[PDB]
Image (tube, rainbow, N blue to C red):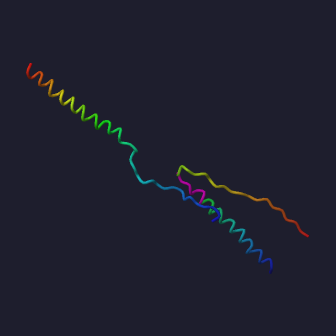
Amino acid sequence: GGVQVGTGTAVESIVRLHDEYSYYKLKGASNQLEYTKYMASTLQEIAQRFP
Amino acid sequence: MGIFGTLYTGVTGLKASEVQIATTGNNISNANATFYTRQRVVQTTNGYITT
């Protein structure tokens, strides 16, 4: 007609949050704690093994 | 007989009724798309004189 129609309402195609790199901070942090705690678990354990 | 012409002219006035179908349907159109700005109705001034 005499006026254009932006027609009403619809939905958007789905997506995930922008960033993971924060999650990357954890991935690196895992490996190192994964080192120390595992190393710890073994080492002190061993330290008691042979007192 | 000529007054018969008035009758179809009245129908044109009746077609002015149809727009309010268009307006109500169009106006209702904006479901919650949270980005909309309305479009709204008018009435007109007039004057007519004779010889």
Q: Residue at x 53, y 52 (%)?
A: B33
Q: List the single residue furthest toward the right.
A: B51
* Residues drawn in magenta: B26-32
Across the whole image, how many numbered discs are drawn on residues? Answer: 0
Q: In front: A35, or B8?
A: A35
Give the quarter of the image for residue B39.
Answer: bottom right
Residue A38 drawn at (x, y percent): 18, 31
Vertical side of B25 occupied by A23: above or below: above
Check the picture and name the quadrant holding the C terminus of chain B.
bottom right
Residue B21 drawn at (x, y percent): 62, 63
Q: Residue at x 65, y 62 (%)?
A: B20
Examine the structure image and report whether residue A48 is included in the region drawn in magenta. no
Vertical side of A19 occupied by B7: above or below: below
Q: In front: A11, or B12?
A: A11
In the image, is A23 to the left or to the right of A40?
Answer: right
Vertical side of A41 occupied by B2: above or below: below
Examine the structure image and report whether residue B30 is included in the region drawn in magenta. yes
Residue A3 drawn at (x, y percent): 63, 61
